[PDB]
Amino acid sequence: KQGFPMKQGVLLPTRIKLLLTKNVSCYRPRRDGERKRKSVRGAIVGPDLAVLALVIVKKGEQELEGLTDTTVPKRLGPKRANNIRKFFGLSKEDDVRDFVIRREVTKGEKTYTKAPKIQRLVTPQRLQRKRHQRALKVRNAQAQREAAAEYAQLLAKRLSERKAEKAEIRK
Amino acid sequence: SDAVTIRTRKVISNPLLARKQFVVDVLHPNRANVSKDELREKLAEVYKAEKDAVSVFGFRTQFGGGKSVGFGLVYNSVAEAKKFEPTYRLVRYGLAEKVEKASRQQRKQKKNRDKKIFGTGKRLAKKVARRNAD
Amino acid sequence: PRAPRTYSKTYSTPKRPYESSRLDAELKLAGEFGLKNKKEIYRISFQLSKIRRAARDLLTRDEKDPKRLFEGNALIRRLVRVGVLSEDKKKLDYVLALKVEDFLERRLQTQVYKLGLAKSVHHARVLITQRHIAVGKQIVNIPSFMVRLDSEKHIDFAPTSPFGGARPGRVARRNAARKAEASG
Amino acid sequence: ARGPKKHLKRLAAPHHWLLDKLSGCYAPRPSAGPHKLRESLPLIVFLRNRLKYALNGREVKAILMQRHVKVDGKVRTDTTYPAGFMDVITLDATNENFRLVYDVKGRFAVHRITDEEASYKLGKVKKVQLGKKGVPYVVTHDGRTIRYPDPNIKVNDTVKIDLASGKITDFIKFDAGKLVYVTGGRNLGRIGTIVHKERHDGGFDLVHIKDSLDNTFVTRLNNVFVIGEQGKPYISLPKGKGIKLSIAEERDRRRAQQ
RNA sequence: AUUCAUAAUAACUUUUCGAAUCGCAUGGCCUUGUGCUGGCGAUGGUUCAUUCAAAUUUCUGCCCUAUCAACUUUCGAUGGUAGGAUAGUGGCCUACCAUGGUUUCAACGGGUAACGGGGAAUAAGGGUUCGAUUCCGGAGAGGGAGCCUGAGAAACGGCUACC
RNA sequence: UAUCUGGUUGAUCCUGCCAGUAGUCAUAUGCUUGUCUCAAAGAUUAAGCCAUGCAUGUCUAAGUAUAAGCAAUUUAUACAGUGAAACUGCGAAUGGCUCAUUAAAUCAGUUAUCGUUUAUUUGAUAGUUCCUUUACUACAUGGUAUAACUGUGGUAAUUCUAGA
């Protein structure tokens, strides 16, 4: 009653005030790091409940027409490339990319597929990116070896130059 | 159009905004002051750059009349003044007609109301409608 | 908040209010020069105080001191420009001896009186305030102008005033209608 | 204040920016950058107040947003990038080039340098260190880090950059009889020609400098920027060559050579 | 000026990082394959320097009051050694001697119709009074206390609790 | 603008106050709806209490949009436009206000950090990562609780919330 939701793990039949956080149910922090103290009901069911939420996991011999005769159609299909691959699972070279899940929705007299933007798909641009980052790395390391080698050559010239000056001194 | 003797001073070439920057001073004896629909096209013909690529403002009348000084500027094209000229001047000169908009008090109040709503809000109207019966 | 706008006073009230010798002189001064207030004298004496204070401090410094060589010359040029002290001096002398009569002698109220376009200090003051005067090309209505000695030859009647053509004046314009109304 | 300030009131901005008291109550706070807060010129106050290329900060942002201005060769598409002393900035419209330099009276003057002059910049080495892997480096006055410097260069020297790479093309040591610039103190903008440096073991080395007019003065070592040897400076000097005319003779020169 | 920078050597690390990210551009030698390479950039997470900052001291300086002459009293109270904590110094806190530290050059108490300063008013010269308040610094968010997140807050148009 | 003057006596000279006098970015108040510019303004008593409404939000060519959102395909059958939300990121520690506390404490001259830095900016900088290890072998590139969104919800009520 009064709307307070039950919470898993409290292990009590009474309402309880708890300091809730992000990644804790019954509370959505409007601000990062914010904690609020809210009243929640314990997970134990008693006479005081107004509504109990139940999932059916094993149907009996009987049937309920509103649930079994109706099957909610697909609302969103898989988006990630590998997620689509395990959704069908036929093969890898069987070009499922251009056979991706398309859903028919029309706002007027014209129809469109509106396929999801497939993610983690290998693109020539993605091959371009990894290729360039490899090239940029080798160009970086090679150049720092030239600058390091050139400086050692400069240091060798300086040491000999200082050695040459003291060669004149002391006969 | 009689002895208006409009002229510009301190003309500097500002190509980063692609315009000519200057101050404009007019001598208008036996005249109150020259208006925009007069000064803008007069500044256009003297410069021969474009027609609506001219802008003037400031224009304080000298104490006791006689002459007036302000600021002016001319663009290379009308399609180039559209990208730089301030909006309020464009609307004032007639280059744009601003649609009516909600007041600051009302705009801020609406933002306060929809910040009170999480989600898009389509489902909230249904729950209230379904719970309005009892 | 925005930086404060500085302001400063321009006049100073005398220490002893009811001085017969000072009261008589100041009201005598106002009559000879057509001033409306004693504050119009107080400011000139306040302006003179800042000047005598400036020269006194400068003159305590020794000769060929860079401070008075620069600041004394600047004060001379400003005072010569406004015509309060005589221009045929180069000795930093007149400054400490400047009298009150010298400053308001250079005011436009008396400047246009002795230039012949006003015929009285009170007529000039009304003439000044009603904008029938241009110093350069510009109409002024300030009784206390401090003409800079380059404008005494530049004085003239305002072109936007009667006696300038195409402008008889509002009372004259009414009589213009009376001229036609008299016959009708 | 619980954290860094992000605003800058007027009357609290550095005086040499030549900002007025009124027409606003916030001066453009220079963001973090190569130059310090006080000794830097924001691009906003340069492009607007110095040249009048713009009337306000919105229109400078319009100038900035199209990548027309670039300091040290890099665009800097932000309102308050702190361009500082000896920085080169470029306006590719008609090829206008600028070197942020100090005038006689201690303010950032407006230069006009050529393309071959705008290629190079002069950097005073703030400290000499070696970093990770024994690699030596020098920190310039504008925060640049240059690896593998010439071993002959020490602190208080002046290296010249090419602004197309990060390397040192040439440098000049710090010693008596070298042309120097004053960056800070009350002698700001004066060109010095070092005559002596007295040490004071433990802090604030002092240097004595006399310009072309045989006027000598003393300033802290951290305020001295060497800019060349006798004769030719490494950079183009501003109008007036930093000679510090007195008010009396500045009054005369203003009267005759208007 | 250093046990500094930075090497190098045993090792230790419960994986820190060491780009599976994004946009525009598709130029070109080829035995036609993204196969050889591609150009500008955006956002990088590490480290060093830099900048914007923060924390930390007293070198000297503060109004009236003796109708305040002694004060600092397991449990800090001056110093030592060691540890813990901290971003870090430090009685900052925890484990001992010595009575250590301050004081008529005014300590310590009491008062302040006391936030400090740049400054203001008033002036012969010296002064007297003021400064809540346009700038700078400090503190606070009704009173206390505690804390999350975050580079940074003991934040209050963030949280928690009591009054 | 380095002034003084009145009041003790029958009269005098003093000491000495009282009173006058001038100023006040010192405040209040008395006497007023006809002028230009400029401008302080709930500090003093109550750092007292607050109805109400505003005062922090935020997007690019470039982190995520199949909004069942609005829109001429042949450059948009993988998406490539605009785009409400929601996530992620950043910011909300700035700003603004006030002066209660506070008497070597704040503060001021900004000594020192050889006593501690890295929203950020700027510059530089990582060929060492088959850690069941001389390919006994994905980087032409291993997944998932959950937000949005669809769905009969609960509560008088909140910017309350798992239930597919």
Image (cartoon, coloured by chain):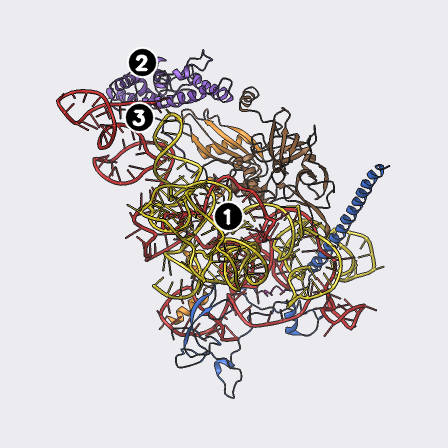
Chain colours: A blue, B orange, C purple, D brown, E yellow, F red
- Secondary element at tag 3: loop
Please report the bounds of the magenta region as a residue range.
A111-119
Per the image, label 1 sits on a secondary structure element best described as loop
Q: Residue furthest top?
A: C88
In terms of sequence position, does the residue under pointer 2 or pointer 3 come before the other?
3
Q: Looking at the picture, does residue D73 appear above or below residue D209?
A: below
Q: Are marks 1 and 3 on the same chain?
A: no
Residue denoted by label 1: D5
Q: Chain of mark 3?
A: C
Disc 1 residue type (three-letter): Lys
Residue bearing the label numbered 3:
C13
Relative height, residue C74 to residue E77 (above, below):
above
Q: For mark 2, what is the residue?
A: C119
**Marks 2/1: CA distance?**
66 Å
Q: Is residue D35 visible?
A: yes
Query: Is residue E117 shown left or right of residue E9?
Result: left
Residue A48 counted in the magenta span? no
- Using the rendered image, report if marks 2 and 1 lie on a common chain: no
Which class describes the residues within 10 Å of circle 3: few (<14), some (14-19), or many (20+)?
few
- Asked whether E55 or F54 is in front, the reply is E55
Residue at x 49%, y 46% (from the top left corner): D7
